[PDB]
Amino acid sequence: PYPV
Image (cartoon, rainbow, N blue to C red):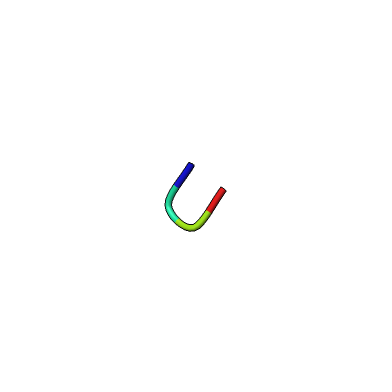
């Protein structure tokens, strides 16, 4: 989530 950061990025994924």
